[PDB]
Amino acid sequence: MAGMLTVGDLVIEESTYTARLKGRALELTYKEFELLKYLAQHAGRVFTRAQLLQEVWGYGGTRTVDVHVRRLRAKLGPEYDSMIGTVRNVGYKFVRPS
Amino acid sequence: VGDLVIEESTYTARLKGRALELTYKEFELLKYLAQHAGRVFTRAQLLQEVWGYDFFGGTRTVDVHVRRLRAKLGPEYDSMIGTVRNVGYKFVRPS
DNA sequence: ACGTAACATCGCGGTAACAC
DNA sequence: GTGTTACCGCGATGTTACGT
Image (cartoon, rainbow over all chains, first blue to last red; front, side, top):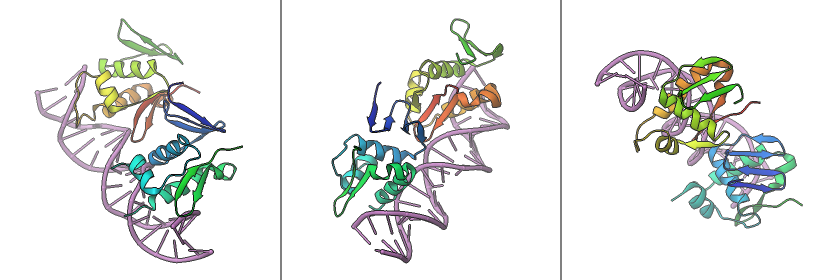
C-alpha cells in the first residue's frame, strides 16, 4: 500500500492507476479519475466548480464538471450512482456509503 | 516470471525458452517495468530512471521503445506492457 | 543502437443545446 | 441551476523509416 484509497467498495489505487468497484474495474478518462479520486480523497466535504477546476484541472465553461460528474455516475452505475452527491447552488461531493 | 525470465548479468530475456533479442535500452525498460510490475510510470520517470538524459521536451523514444518491445513479445505477450493514457506505461501480469 | 521524422489512429474532453 | 447527450477539434499513442 503506497497511495491506495478505499471508501465502501470503491478502491482508488493511484499506484497501479486503477479504480475498481468490488472487482469490476472502472475504465475512466484521465479527468474522471483525477475528479473521482479528489472527491473521495475528501469524502463528505462539498466543493464548488471553481475549487474543483483550480485543483483537478489547474490554474467560462464551468459545466465541464457537470459533464464529468455525469460520465462518472453513469460509469459507476445505479448501485453506486449515489456516491457523488449534488448540492444545489454549491457544487458536488463524494458521499460515504452506510 | 509469468513465462518471462530476465537475465541480469547476460542482459537478456526469454519467454518460455525463446530468447528475446533485445537492445539494451529495451532490456532496461522491460526490466524496470517488470521489477515494479503493476505500477505505472510516467515518461519523465522512465526517462531519468531508464535513460540517462533528461530530454525535457522531445524524446518520444520511450513510446518508440515500447513498440519495439511489444513487437518482439508478439501478439501473444504484447499485453505484458499496458498503456495508461496521459500518464505512461506499466507491466501487466497475466491473467 | 537509438532517437528523430512523419504520419495514421483514436480517444479526450469541452462546448453546444435542450429538458426540467 | 443542473442532468444529459451530441459533436468533433485536438492531442496523446502507435507506428515505421531513416539518419547518425
